[PDB]
Image (cartoon, rainbow over the protein chains, first blue to last red):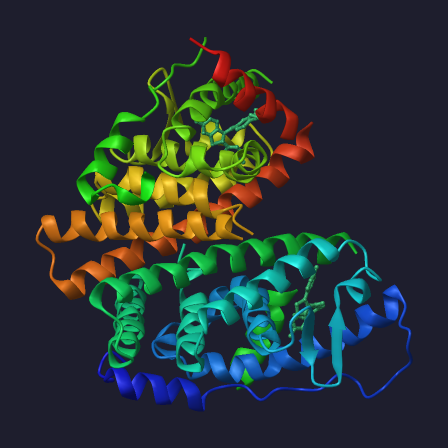
Length: 225
Length: 223
Ligand SMILES: O=C(c1ccc(OCCN2CCCCC2)cc1)c1c(-c2ccc(O)cc2)sc2cc(O)ccc12
Ligand SMILES: O=C(c1ccc(OCCN2CCCCC2)cc1)c1c(-c2ccc(O)cc2)sc2cc(O)ccc12
């Protein structure tokens, strides 16, 4: 785990990338609040399966005990679906690419009980990713970080060194791209601060989701794996 | 102006803006914390106005920044002042609570535990006051940041990163240790946001835009 070079880390992660799934094939439009919720729910659930496989490929992840793994996923799943959303939405200004066959815009997002707020936040995040020209290899570094860090609250120590290893890898990608040492640290901070907002959106979303078992589910899923 | 400060000028500006540590004036426990929070707010606005870049913002923007960061600000200060009081939260010098005392409020334990773990992690990394003050300003500037305006703030933020690294180098960490520590501290900003988000839920379960607007307004007519 802590034996991978910057480059080995990066390729490992890129390989672990989950596939991009599709929305239940053309149901009916315009959707309703429940119909859209249903497409979104079906999608998320199917994506949750791949997430488990990806998690299991995240350096450090499978060194933890099954129950700690469940804890990290329990807490990060929504952040992780969201960073994937934002990233695949980058080249669709004004719209979110929940799936290739389900590209919604601000107005569609209002069909559901106050997701406008989040949708907008989400919109702004890919926008900033676009603005910063976020790169694939950095994106995968940010996801792994979200996975290890949202739930981190000799094992504690282990995760902190994997986390330090991903920072190393993020700065290594920046240097190799020619950034100045000053630009390196600035970009590193611009990225980690975006995790603050990502977290923010998942807490808002979790609230919106519950206004409208996971442990056991993930345990079952993680153990089955 | 803000963008022209050196790393060391930034730090002292900041150290200078520190609010005073207030005391508990003593829904009893909830009373105590509401009174404390309320009086702290008043100084927060004041310190806000001394964060480089902050006053270059429109009044609306200033209120949006505090509207979203106030609780993260209160918490990071609680955390910091709790550091050397393992097992307890030092809400005030005359109001040091423990895990169990936090239990007397429904839902407070989980946040309380979270608050405890954050000060623990601050202890663990030997967070320095200079670094602390740096992290508070980033919180103010970042939690509500979501067009030469957007850009200003982002530059102020870059300068804070610069200052953060400066203190680290100055302290003698290696280049590698610098980005590592920088990253360790900024991931703690997600947990802080997390506690704030959870804390507002809890606050509103129990039972401000203009409040700050007036406050930010009144500050220009204050002696
Ligand atoms: O709409 C969803 C969403 C819907 C249902 C979900 O979960 C339903 C239940 N499921 C139970 C087993 C554990 C996995 C979750 C999760 C996300 C998505 C998001 C969301 C956005 C705004 C908002 O206000 C609330 C949520 S973002 C997102 C990205 C995706 O790839 C998929 C769904 C989503
Ligand atoms: O208890 C408080 C607190 C209590 C009442 C508050 O609100 C007072 C209402 N007021 C209205 C106008 C805006 C300013 C707040 C805010 C914080 C504090 C915290 C808290 C912790 C756990 C939790 O679940 C909820 C809150 S943390 C904290 C730090 C302080 O310096 C002061 C109070 C606090």
